[PDB]
Figure 1 (cartoon, each protein chain N blue to C red):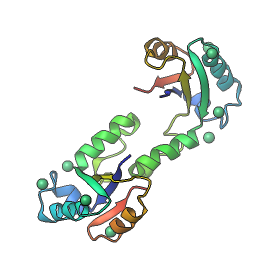
Figure 2: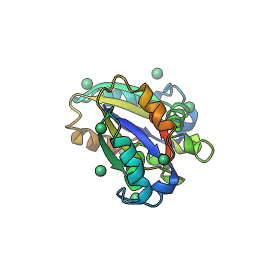
Figure 3: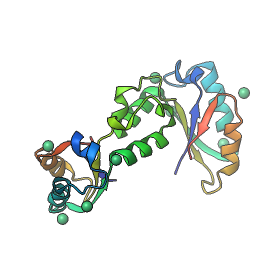
Figure 4: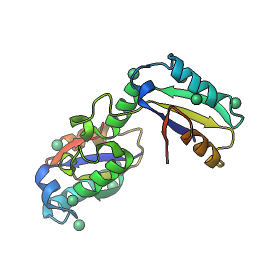
Length: 99
Length: 99
Ligand SMILES: [Br-]
Ligand SMILES: [Br-]
Ligand SMILES: [Br-]
Ligand SMILES: [Br-]
Ligand SMILES: [K+]
Ligand SMILES: [K+]
Ligand SMILES: [K+]
Ligand SMILES: [K+]
């Protein structure tokens, strides 16, 4: 069980490796959480590819631009994710958190 | 661990509880196999919800007809599931098997 923190459109479209300073700074910000053990970046292309695989019926219909880049986040205890989700939603540069 | 047997549309569109002739007949063919311990039914509304829960990106284009219903099947010997998979794939009413 891992959390997924969605990023904003311009980072999604233009940063394929989280090498913009803001995306890196945002990865660091998340890593500082007392309840976070690991943070992994997943770009727009890869996330689209992973989804299309798992559900091969939108191969044409759905485009990658519907898929935000994100951080896949391993928490200390995934049953206590409430505080984390709250912080993320209050964090600038974070679009949403997967519910 | 559990096996997932996806159903063709003729059952997926009609039946919310496996209460149509086609669904039950298919359910009975699976349950009576010696290599099957238990069979659970998963309607298309539950399939839509599980999928959108994991990929809300698809909510743009996915209708209730985009996700097939399924049987969640508990095998007697899970490690040895290769002949079961093939049997199901050759069964009328079966769309696909997970993996
Ligand atoms: Br990308
Ligand atoms: Br239904
Ligand atoms: Br059931
Ligand atoms: Br038959
Ligand atoms: K980097
Ligand atoms: K930490
Ligand atoms: K935010
Ligand atoms: K049986």
